Length: 49
Image 1 (cartoon, rainbow, N blue to C red):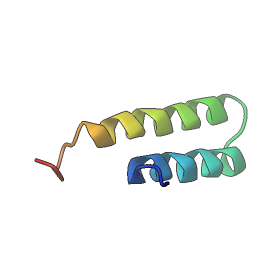
Image 2 (image 1 turned 120 degrees about the vertical axis):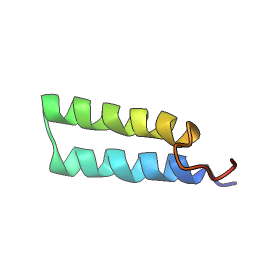
Image 3 (image 1 turned 135 degrees about the horizontal axis):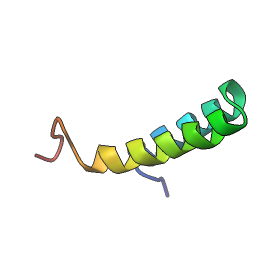
Image 4 (image 1 turned 90 degrees about the vertical axis):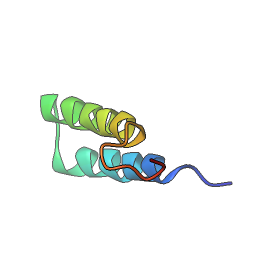
Protein backbone atom coordinates (compact mmCIF):
# COMPACT_ATOMS: atom_id res chain seq x y z
CA UNK A 1 0.00 0.00 0.00
CA UNK A 2 1.53 3.22 -1.12
CA UNK A 3 0.15 6.73 -1.52
CA UNK A 4 0.49 8.76 -4.73
CA UNK A 5 3.76 10.45 -5.45
CA UNK A 6 2.03 13.81 -5.10
CA UNK A 7 1.08 12.72 -1.60
CA UNK A 8 4.70 11.80 -1.07
CA UNK A 9 5.53 15.35 -2.28
CA UNK A 10 3.00 16.66 0.21
CA UNK A 11 4.51 14.61 3.05
CA UNK A 12 8.01 15.85 2.32
CA UNK A 13 6.75 19.38 1.82
CA UNK A 14 4.91 19.50 5.15
CA UNK A 15 7.84 17.84 6.96
CA UNK A 16 10.12 20.51 5.55
CA UNK A 17 7.72 23.26 6.46
CA UNK A 18 7.68 22.01 10.06
CA UNK A 19 11.44 22.37 10.26
CA UNK A 20 12.14 25.31 7.94
CA UNK A 21 9.10 27.40 8.76
CA UNK A 22 7.16 28.30 11.87
CA UNK A 23 4.20 30.38 12.99
CA UNK A 24 2.37 32.06 10.12
CA UNK A 25 5.07 30.84 7.78
CA UNK A 26 4.36 27.26 8.81
CA UNK A 27 0.64 27.37 8.30
CA UNK A 28 1.08 29.09 4.98
CA UNK A 29 3.95 26.78 3.98
CA UNK A 30 1.93 23.63 4.66
CA UNK A 31 -1.04 25.26 2.99
CA UNK A 32 1.09 25.83 -0.12
CA UNK A 33 1.99 22.13 0.04
CA UNK A 34 -1.74 21.39 0.03
CA UNK A 35 -2.13 23.75 -2.92
CA UNK A 36 0.73 22.10 -4.77
CA UNK A 37 -0.81 18.71 -4.07
CA UNK A 38 -3.97 19.99 -5.82
CA UNK A 39 -1.84 21.53 -8.55
CA UNK A 40 -0.07 18.26 -9.22
CA UNK A 41 -3.45 16.80 -10.02
CA UNK A 42 -4.11 19.82 -12.17
CA UNK A 43 -1.27 18.83 -14.47
CA UNK A 44 0.20 21.96 -16.08
CA UNK A 45 2.78 19.86 -17.87
CA UNK A 46 0.80 16.70 -18.40
CA UNK A 47 1.80 13.28 -17.18
CA UNK A 48 -1.49 11.67 -17.95
CA UNK A 49 -2.18 14.19 -20.63
